[PDB]
Image (cartoon, rainbow, N blue to C red):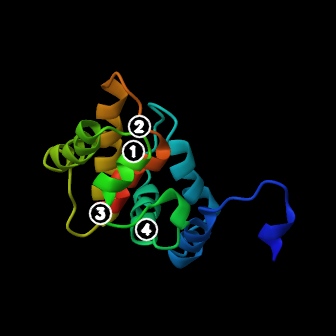
Amino acid sequence: SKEVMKQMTINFAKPMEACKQELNVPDAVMQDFFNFWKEGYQITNREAGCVILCLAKKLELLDQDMNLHHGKAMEFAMKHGADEAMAKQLLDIKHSCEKVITIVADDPCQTMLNLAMCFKAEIHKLDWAPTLDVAVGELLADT
């Protein structure tokens, strides 16, 4: 009822507000994920990964109009303006990063955050930009 009322309302917020309470974490650390997308910005917090990995399961929650579903990244990414070469590149960057980053057996949040900040590192270098729908979407879809 409340998210009806205002002129601007956010479709992708339903898994995101759900993650914050589901994980039993403060509003401070879900906003660490919002700050994370700012380039070079020094997000080191273990909770940032914990929220990030949480969306990847909860893509089911997302609106069908953006076409995001888990495992469907190659098809999804192309709908968001990636070419087929560039789509496989985001998946290639991820798996290339996974082997160089610290992976923690105990803590999947460090594995996700360390990967994500490595993944963003590579698309920063590139002459083309994926959008937040597609750059995160291929990561989150292929979690």
**Residue type at tag 2:** Pro
Q: From the viewer's perspective, is the residue at label 2 or at label 4 nearer?
A: 2
Q: Compared to 98, does 23 lie above or below? A: below
Q: Give the CA distance from mark 4 to mark 1.
A: 16 Å
The residue at the point 42 percent across, 40 percent down is: 81
Residue that carries the numbered disc 4 in the rendered image: 54
Q: How crowded is mark 2: few (under 14 residues within 10 Å), some or many (20 or more)?
A: some
Q: Nearer the viewer, residue 16 or 3?
A: 3
**Residue type at tag 1:** Ala
Q: Nearer the viewer, residue 75 or 3?
A: 75
Residue that carries the numbered disc 3 in the rendered image: 143
**Tag 1's secondary structure?**
helix
Q: Please, which residue is most extreme toward the top here? A: 127
Residue that carries the numbered disc 2 in the rendered image: 130
Q: Is residue 78 left or right of residue 58?
A: left
Q: How crowded is mark 3: few (under 14 residues within 10 Å), some or many (20 or more)?
A: some
Q: Give the CA distance from mark 2 to mark 4.
A: 21 Å
Q: How crowded is mark 4: few (under 14 residues within 10 Å), some or many (20 or more)?
A: many
Quarter of the image for the C terminus: give it: bottom left
Q: From the viewer's perspective, is the residue at label 4 or at label 1 nearer?
A: 1
Residue 139 visible in the snapshot:
no
Q: Give the CA distance from mark 3 to mark 1.
A: 13 Å
Q: Residues within 10 Å of mark 1 (few under 14, many from 20)?
A: many
Q: Give the CA distance from mark 2 to mark 3.
A: 18 Å
Q: Nearer the viewer, residue 138 or 41?
A: 138
Q: In which quarter of the image is residue 140?
A: bottom left
Quarter of the image for the N terminus: give it: bottom right
**Tag 3's secondary structure?**
loop
- Tag 1–tag 2 contact (CB < 8 Å): yes
Q: Residue 135 carries which label?
A: 1
**Residue type at tag 4:** Cys
Percent coordinates x, y for residue 114 in the rendering: 30, 48
